[PDB]
Image (tube, rainbow, N blue to C red; front, side, top):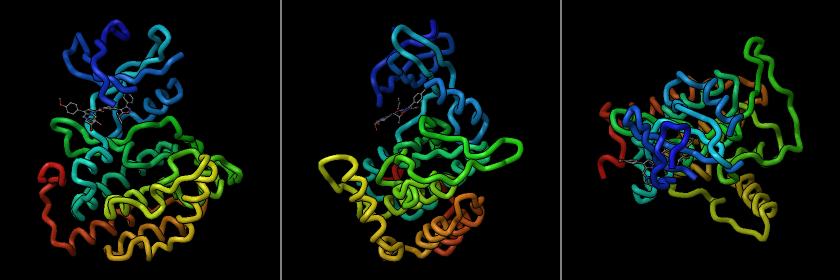
Length: 280
Ligand SMILES: COc1ccc(-c2cc(C(=O)Nc3cc(-c4c(-c5ccc(F)cc5)noc4C(C)C)ccn3)n3c2CN2C[C@@H](O)[C@@H](O)[C@@H]2C3)cc1
């Protein structure tokens, strides 16, 4: 099995397959879509940013649309499970700094991601093992004009495009997603790493609609101070800041990063850039 006259298809690794660039000799990741183009154009617009994967090829192969990406490593959800679903505070703070910057970069390129979750952040392999990458622009959306920075308008009655567990409250309410919502989702991700789960995780119903209402109801009835009880105040400050942003507001990314850098300092952690999964 060969795609693009250049890549040998290997075994399933996640429908994601390991592949081999036959000419260069390097391994790649291959995504197959049964007869992706839109997503490739967003990746291309994002290319050249820290933690943005490079796309090596995209085309047509039989009854499949194919995309080939540089090989990355396990996702943060994979590594969370590998660490028995608990991260040290230091690892959470190291991840927070990078993840805020990845989201800022996407926003600087005029898009919102709309599905921020642990499964969409992958660690690099090899010399890039300490670098957090962001993937999956299949739900991303342009929120402003590149030159004038004129914002898309406020709208309601929007379907939940994302993952319910990490969706912002405004997303549950059907409001058009904007920059604030990517960051609020990240806030839930960070408390998820701290807690091992979220209070609304695992709620079930007969149909998705009832399930989402269940999650929305619990999310709305859980104050930030209760969610973050027993953890450094910075996590609540982060979430409160994100919920205070208006639809069109430009987030103060530097302030949010400084929250966690300040806590990093007060905790006495060392500048050795070692994550938990490398030191079980
Ligand atoms: C020999 O040493 C090694 C050590 C570790 C690994 C290695 C590499 C991977 C991996 O998935 N890479 C990867 C995946 C994607 C990708 C895309 C995508 C989008 C557009 C494209 F064009 C192409 C792909 N869409 O989704 C994904 C992910 C979320 C599945 C993109 C780039 N890279 N995984 C492992 C080890 N696994 C154990 C278990 O935890 C498994 O989950 C984990 C997965 C490989 C070798």
